[PDB]
Length: 357
Image (tube, rainbow, N blue to C red):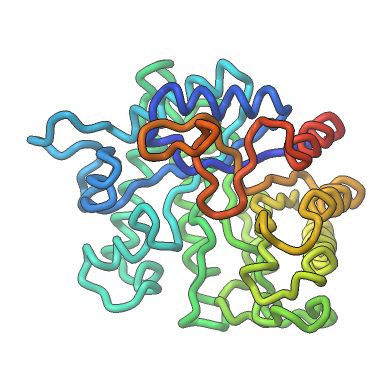
């Protein structure tokens, strides 16, 4: 099973019309897998979307006494039930490295810590994360009757979006946390694949250096991620990596070739370990002084020809509503990476590649 996929982060709090638009767009484009957020941590983040999943420790869903709110598990249930109908598989990510939708820092605030990376080390935090993941994995979808643990529309659980641990550049803190949490998830759910959800950084591997000497920090262990060690964990089934040369310090004239080397290096390493590998986010800013579609073509050709298992662009959006609606009625392109099901050369390329994978 090899695929073209995409990402969408608003499938757990937007309306039925907007969720149906994304999933129908995915089906129309041939996109087989969508990677979505399965978290909304913190009372202020929940209140901002009027949608609740984990507003305080041990509170899963809407707090007693709050009326007129959405329950993010109900919205995720709708998304799963619609994906099931439309034939789209989902990867569901269980916490954010970043502060959007609360993330690890929200857990650290609840438990009175003093650094983001306390999320990996404080046993009271680790316990709360497991309590949340167990609630979610066991949740019975109100539209299907099937608990997420048994739902084949979910392709994989992912531990943490773009996890980093800059305070331990040995990589050991993350190896230990990933071992613990991936084994924990396998103990709850022996049916589903588990992956980390990290960006794929290396930690000074002999013979692996960046194209052009740019973004050496992604190759030299600065973020505390040792991708090869994470992929060798028994309870991790496939490798994940992300690709954003414009964020990482690469020059525009080197975006294509830096990304090409990055893909080649990840596929070579995962093939030696013997596990599948997915490029599960990639993006070039719409305004880059290079041909974005031609870079995307290059990168998708490399994944396809080298035997990578999937390539998923960040990100797919559909129709918008209310304050998230642009000049064409779509959810806006806030970050410069949005693709929609239109006549753009990027949309045309994705449709073309979805026919090949």
